Image (cartoon, coloured by chain):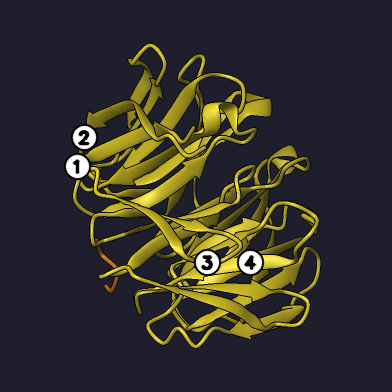
Amino acid sequence: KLDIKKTFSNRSDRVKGIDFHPTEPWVLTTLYSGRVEIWNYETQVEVRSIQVTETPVRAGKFIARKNWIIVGSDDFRIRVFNYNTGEKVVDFEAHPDYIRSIAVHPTKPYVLSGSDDLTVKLWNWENNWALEQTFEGHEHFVMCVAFNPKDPSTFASGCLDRTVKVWSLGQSTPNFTLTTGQERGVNYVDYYPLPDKPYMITASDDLTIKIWDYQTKSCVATLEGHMSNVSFAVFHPTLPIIISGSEDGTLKIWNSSTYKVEKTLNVGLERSWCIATHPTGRKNYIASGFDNGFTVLSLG
Amino acid sequence: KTKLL
C-alpha cells in the first residue's frame, strides 16, 4: 500500500511554512529569508515567487476561494497576495511580536493568527480584515492554531506554556485547556479529520507526540522515537497513518491504530519544520519543508 | 528570543 515516491524536491533557504493548493498542482513554501515560492510540482516550474520581507516568514496558506495566499512574518505583519496577478491585497501589523501560525476557516471569511505576543487573533476579510476577536489566556508563545474541521466554530491553539486551549468563536475563555505533560511546550496541534474519533495530536520539543481524546481529555497514546524537537505531527486525511517531522532530520510515518512507527525517512535536507497533506488525498501527496529545501512525496 | 530557528 505504502509505496513512497519522490514527486519533486528542490533546494532553497529554510522552509518554515508549506501548503497545498486544493485544485492546482501547486505547493506554497514560505522561507526564513523572507521569500515565498509557489511551485507546480507536476511540471517542476515556479508559478510565482515574492521577496515579501527580509525577516522570516513562518506561516503561509492558500485561500483558494479568493485566489490568495496569506503569509505571516517576524516583522509582525500579515500580508495577502493574489497569486494570479501578484497584487498585494493587504499588508498590516497583526501583533507586536512574531507570527508563528495561520489558519483559514473552511467556509467563513476568517483567519486566525497565533503569536509570540501570547494571543490568537481572528481577522475577517469581508470586514476589511478587521480584528474581530483576541483570544487571551496563554502564557507563552502560541506556536500553532488549527480549526476543528468537524466543527470549525471551534479551534485549538498549541503553546510553549505546555497547554492546548480549545476555543469557541465569539467566546473569550477556552472551552477547555489540555495539560499535555509535554514540559518543553507544544509546537503543533492537529485534528483527526474523520467523524469516528474525537482526536487531536500534539508535538513537542520534549521529543514526544501525544494523541488526545478531546471529549474526555485523556491521552490515548504517546509516540516516541524522534531524537530532537518534533516540529509537527498530523493525521493523514485518507490513510490510516500519522506523519511527523523533527529537527533530527527525519519524517516518521506511524500506524494510526497501533501507534507503532512504520517508516523513517531521512530525505537529506537537514531539520524538518513543516508539513502539508493534499486536501483530498490526490495521489496521496504530502509535502514537508526543511533547512535546505522541500520535498513533495506521493505515499502510494 | 526562544525558537528563533
Please tell me which residue is depicted at 50% across the width and 84% down the height of the picture: A139
The answer to whether residue A60 is visible is no
Q: Is residue A73 above or below residue A82?
A: below
The verdict on a common chain for dots 3 and 1 is yes
Chain of the residue under the numbered disc 1 shown in the image: A
Residue A178 in the image, given as x and y percentages of width and height: 63, 83
Please tell me which residue is depicted at 64% across the width and 42% down the height of the picture: A238
Which dot marks residue A200? Answer: 4
Kindly report the distance in space between the C-alpha atoms of the residues bearing marks 3 and 4: 14 Å
| Mark 2: amino acid | Ser
| Mark 4: amino acid | Met
Residue A130 in the image, given as x and y percentages of width and height: 67, 50
The verdict on a common chain for dots 3 and 4 is yes
Please tell me which residue is depicted at 34% across the width and 70% down the height of the picture: A225
Which dot marks residue A12? Answer: 2
Kindly report the distance in space between the C-alpha atoms of the residues bearing marks 2 and 4: 31 Å
Chain of the residue under the numbered disc 3 shown in the image: A
Q: Are marks 2 and 3 in contact (CB under 8 Å)?
A: no
| Mark 3: amino acid | Tyr
In depth, the one of A226 and A261 nearer the eye is A261
Q: Is residue A221 above or below residue B4?
A: below
Tag 4's secondary structure?
Answer: strand
Please tell me which residue is depicted at 49% across the width and 88% down the height of the picture: A181
The verdict on a common chain for dots 2 and 4 is yes
